[PDB]
Amino acid sequence: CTFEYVSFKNLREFVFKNIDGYFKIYSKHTPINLVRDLPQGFSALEPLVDLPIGINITRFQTLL
Amino acid sequence: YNYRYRKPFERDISTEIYQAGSKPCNGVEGFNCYFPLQSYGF
Ligand SMILES: *[C@@H]1O[C@H](CO)[C@@H](O[C@@H]2O[C@H](CO)[C@@H](O)[C@H](O)[C@H]2NC(C)=O)[C@H](O)[C@H]1NC(C)=O
Image (cartoon, rainbow over all chains, first blue to last red; front, side):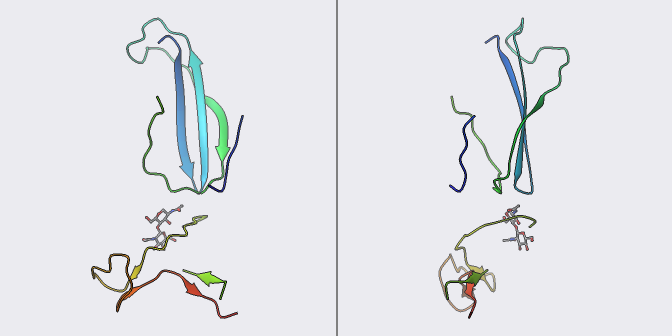
């Protein structure tokens, strides 16, 4: 509790990774034709955030 | 006695026991079963 912060067509994409207590986040957003599964093409995710929190992660869950 | 000691930029304040052997220490004190923090005699 030592840290706190505040800032189907929408395919919204993310990458998350953690290194020596830093925790890095990247993303992209697009509208799409087919909604069922990952549509064929190409685009790159771009950085958002890094948090120096120090946690030793092994699990996660989506908040519906 | 307020000061104490037990990876790169790891921190963990856990009370989980130092076992000195494969005993069922189960997080509880005993012979070969010791609390992880020790105090500096400053
Ligand atoms: C994540 O947790 C593990 C334990 O599950 C930590 O492991 C310790 O790492 C140091 C390396 O300097 C060893 O000397 C200790 O013996 C390890 N502990 C045990 C119980 O084996 C690990 O360091 C943690 N990583 C971070 C970044 O917090």
